[PDB]
Image (cartoon, rainbow over the protein chains, first blue to last red):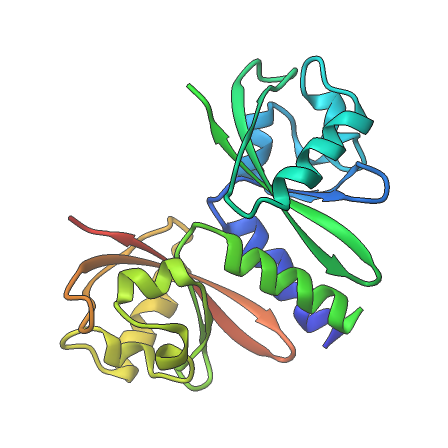
Length: 115
Length: 115
């Protein structure tokens, strides 16, 4: 059940063509992502896991960026933040949604190209 | 951990814009899906959960259809089956991938419009 649902989660995230990054509300760090997100961000999973999400985006810092996404996720309008990914040099639209798991909050962020 | 990973799975599947249906290899029935899949199939989650996947598609039967998807998933080429969804009357492309969880196999099927 632990491993069962873990396995379902892993496969659905990996197979999904929707570019997604999962971010810790506590630390602002990337806790998971899929390869579609990796492609838009310009990095492999191994480089992005554990990385501060704000530092992937030019001119952003953890405090303000996490506050921005937290506030946007509260509008429940799928409102996006416009960003520029340092590695890929692609302008992107990031749409955050907050949910609770294991006593903490995570932000599931969808990524789309902006241009 | 059971609930934690279950919660992650639920949210990722629901939020993902990639239309996905999860099918039991054992029964050929739909065990899960997201609303993007529901839209293409022409049914709500409540009508589709527990339904035989083959019976959603005109002219298909469980035996041959499950054998078709199982064989296609083995080619590892993302080869699609062309189908016509009874409820929505949309021609679709279904791409199956097989994985193991909790001692059984599931097919995670991506759905795309065909026309």
